[PDB]
Length: 246
Ligand code: NA
Image (tube, rainbow, N blue to C red; front, side):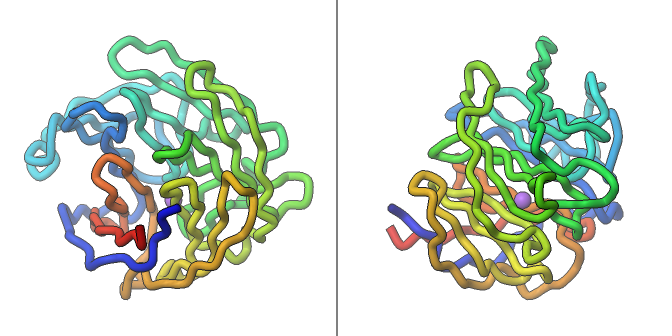
């Protein structure tokens, strides 16, 4: 059971003007160099870059999505974009290059009226993929607070388990998932201060630094392919190395 015990210094890949956005790469065992970007809290377009030099030179192809996205909690896995359909409790899986979009409903989830999972990034849902599964982090519309995690079946894009962490969303700045462990940041998004073992269904101790900057953190996402954290911090696109104890 490998645990993160510290985070290394960030490497900045690009500075853009936009406060909020995402930048994402493939994590499946698919040596794909493409980068996908969204800008702002909502929209219908994704920018596809062929590789990092393309991103550095603002050379993209615009992809029109079948449904508007909201927030900065998306993920790419197996040539597909997973994202929150704005104004609904629907999550979309949009497969690139063929458009076979699938959807699923999270009936018990907050999704509008600024009752955010992560207020700092105006995000209601955070899709995350890692070594142990495909996950969706969200907050309960039953109590308006508790952070829940759905574990998905990849083939059918359906929810197998709902996992209640019992952690209040008011205490969470953002989060990521690595080796089956949910790591949650403080409200200032400077330290990881809470963790939860998603397979054993139990809290586990975690307290370590993420970063020194308190600039607005829009996106925080683990990639199992290179074991780095990807972030968007007030227009600064960063990569952090991660240190596992095992
Ligand atoms: Na996140």
